Each structure stands twice: as structure tokens, then as C-alpha cells.
Image (spheres, coloured by chain):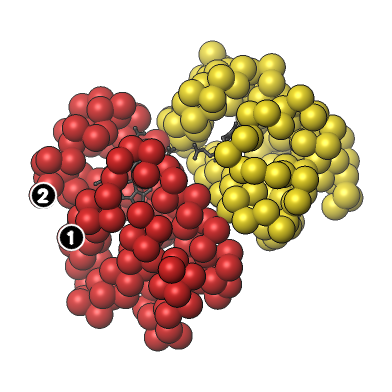
Chain colours: A yellow, B red
Amino acid sequence: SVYDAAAQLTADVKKDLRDSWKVIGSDKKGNGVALMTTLFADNQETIGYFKRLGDVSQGMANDKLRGHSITLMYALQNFIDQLDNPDDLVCVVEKFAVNHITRKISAAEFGKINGPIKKVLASKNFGDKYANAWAKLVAVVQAAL
Amino acid sequence: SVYDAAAQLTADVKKDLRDSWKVIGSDKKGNGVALMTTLFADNQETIGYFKRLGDVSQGMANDKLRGHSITLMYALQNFIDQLDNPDDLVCVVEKFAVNHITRKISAAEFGKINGPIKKVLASKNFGDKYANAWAKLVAVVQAAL
Ligand code: HEM
Ligand code: HEM
């Protein structure tokens, strides 16, 4: 249940999400591309789904990948801004879930993003505590897939 | 080209875009839904394109419409944040252009959003100068359609 998953975002979890996002969200282009390139590097079997972006190994040099990566960061900005209202968080999560359901992305494969998130957080000196908080937000999307 | 249309946005236009967005963008849910409902009220012929959202006359109560409307406002937030780097603006504009090209939305049809934009701006006392500024930004997307 997406509603039960959303209920897992307690005061402490929301605080950790906000605190880490203040830093990570300050460079959407840089960290967004870092998140994607890490996903492709550690989970090569997911590259096939991104055929529209072309040669993803080009990283920042690939215009389609950069446009996609920046936009992905605004989806996370959206989630963070809706943390105060569960009903609004759920409706935006369901909107993005559809974007992935149509691409045949399962809850299990969506969850592969947790590894890259932990690595990007770690590079900014945010440890397991923060990685786990983000895993709980990702779990809300998984509940909708 | 799209780059030409983006590189043409002047300092004054960018200032008017940012000043009006500071206000309109501060209530993404309220103004996002108002923008969409106004589009449907004045251009009823576009309703059919949004069948995925269900009964759009339900307004704020329609969770699918609310989720879509909030997300649309973050696409605009994205555009506003990339104003000083045409290269970044172009790659995000092209990303969203694809989202509309796949739905067979022509450049002329996309321009139908200018009427609703003018009305939403007017609700907060932003006049024709501001509506003209926004039409120039919409024109950047039209260059990609
Ligand atoms: C933090 C997690 C993630 C977020 C917030 C997210 C967000 C997004 C957004 C905003 C889009 C654009 C939707 C559209 O315009 O249609 C997108 C596209 C896509 N996502 Fe994700 N995504 C995430 C993780 C993943 C993962 C882990 C996979 C695959 C295992 C995945 C697969 C896709 C695919 C295949 C596309 C389509 C790309 C294209 O052809 O343009 N996403 N995602
Ligand atoms: C300020 C201008 C506009 C912006 C920023 C914008 C933004 C968006 C965004 C972000 C989406 C979601 C894309 C996706 O997830 O696949 C969307 C979907 C869509 N847009 Fe727009 N849009 C605008 C104007 C228009 C206009 C004027 C029309 C039609 C006359 C239009 C028709 C559509 C349709 C049919 C969808 C698909 C809805 C669905 O089934 O989920 N858009 N738009």
C-alpha cells in the first residue's frame, strides 16, 4: 500500500531527507548525472531500458542524458516539497509510477537505484543513516509499481 | 533553432519571468490546477487529450489531475532555473518536447497555453508585459515542436 508506505516517513526520516537534499539538490545537473552514470555502471543490465538516450557512456557530454538527469532531480525536489501533505505526496508518486509502469519497470528493478543513491550520498559525507531514509522514500514509489 | 530561441531571451525578459514565478511558483498546487482548469474551460477541444486523468471537471478533488498539475509546475521551475545557461535550457526543453511530440501535440496547439497563462498571471496582478515574457519562453518549446 502506497498509503502505508507513506506513513513510514516519520519526523526523523523527513528531517534526514530534507537535510541531505539541501546539499545534494544544490547541484542537480552534477549529482543527477552522477546518479545515472553510477546506475549504468553498477547495473549494466538496466541500460537497455534507456535506449532513447543514446550512448549513455558519454555521460555529461550526452545532451539527452543531461536533460533527463536534470529533470529526474526535479522529480525528487517535487517529492521533498510534498512531505508535509501525504495526500499530495501520494498523487505525485502515482504520477511518476505510471511513467515507469509504461516502461515495464518493476518495483524490484526500480529499487536498484538504492545502490547509486548510497554512493552519491557517501561521496558527500552522508552515511548509511541518510541512505536508509532515502530508501524509505523510494519504497513509496515501489509500492505504486 | 531551439538554441536561437533560448539565446534570444534577454536580461529584462528573464527578470520578468523570475519575478512573476517567485509569486506564481510559490503555490504550485493551487496555480497549477488553476492553469489546467482554465485550459479546459476555454479550450474544450483539448479535454480529449487528457483522458488518462479521468474527469477533469472534478478539479482539485481529482488526484490524477492534481498530481499532473503539480508536476507541470516543476517543469516550469526547471525552465526558470536554467535561464542563465542556454545549453542546459535547451536540453530540458527538448526532453519535455518529446513528451508532447509522442502525444501528437503540434507547436500551434502547445501555444494554446498562452491564454490560460495570461489569466493566471492576471489573478496576481501581473500584466501584459509579463504575459509577453512567458509567451517568449513558451516559444522556446514551440521551436522544438
Ligand atoms: C530515484 C528514482 C527515480 C526517479 C525519481 C525517476 C524519475 C524519472 C523521470 C522524471 C522520468 C521521465 C518520465 C517521462 O518523461 O516519461 C524517468 C524516465 C525513465 N525512468 Fe526513471 N526514475 C527513477 C529510477 C529509475 C530506475 C531505477 C529505472 C530503471 C531500473 C528507471 C527507468 C526509467 C526509464 C526507462 C525511463 C525512460 C527514459 C526515456 O526514454 O526518456 N527509472 N524516470
Ligand atoms: C506551459 C506548457 C506546458 C508544460 C510545461 C507541459 C508539461 C507537461 C508535463 C510535465 C507532462 C507530463 C509528461 C509525461 O509524464 O509524460 C505533460 C503531459 C501532457 N501534456 Fe503538457 N505541458 C504544457 C502544455 C500542454 C498543452 C497546451 C497541451 C495540449 C494542448 C499539452 C498536452 C499534454 C498531454 C496530452 C499530456 C499527457 C497527459 C497524460 O496522459 O498524463 N500540454 N505536460
* Cα gap from disc 1 to disc 2, whole angstroms: 8 Å
Discs 1 and 2 share one subunit: yes
Q: Is residue A19 above or below residue B122?
A: above
Write the residue at 80% across / 40% down: A38
Q: Position of residue A90 (x, y in %)?
A: 48, 29
| Residue A80 appears in the picture as rendered | no
> Which part of the image, by quadrant, shows the C terminus of chain A?
top right
> Which part of the image, by quadrant, shows the N terminus of chain A?
top right
| Disc 1 and disc 2 in contact, CB within 8 angstroms | yes
Q: Is residue A125 above or below residue B114?
A: above
Q: Is residue B108 above or below residue B7?
A: above
Say which chain tag 1 marks.
Answer: B
The residue that label 1 is drawn on is B115
Write the residue at 17% across / 49% down: B38
**Callout 1: few (<14), some (14-19), or many (20+) C-alpha neighbours within 10 Å?**
some
What kind of element bears circle 2?
A: helix
Q: From this viewpoint, which residue is outermost toward the top?
A: A1
Q: Position of residue A59 (x, y in %)?
A: 75, 51
Write the residue at 31% across / 35% down: B65
Q: Is residue A138 above or below residue A73?
A: above
Q: In terms of depth relative to the viewer, which is nearer, B43 or A51?
A: A51
- Amino acid type of the residue that numbered disc 2 sits on in the rendered structure: Asp
Say which chain tag 2 marks.
Answer: B
- Amino acid type of the residue that numbered disc 1 sits on in the rendered structure: Gly
| Residue A27 appears in the picture as rendered | yes
Name the mark on residue A39.
Answer: none
The residue that label 2 is drawn on is B42
What kind of element bears circle 1?
A: helix
Q: Position of residue A39 (x, y in %)?
A: 77, 36
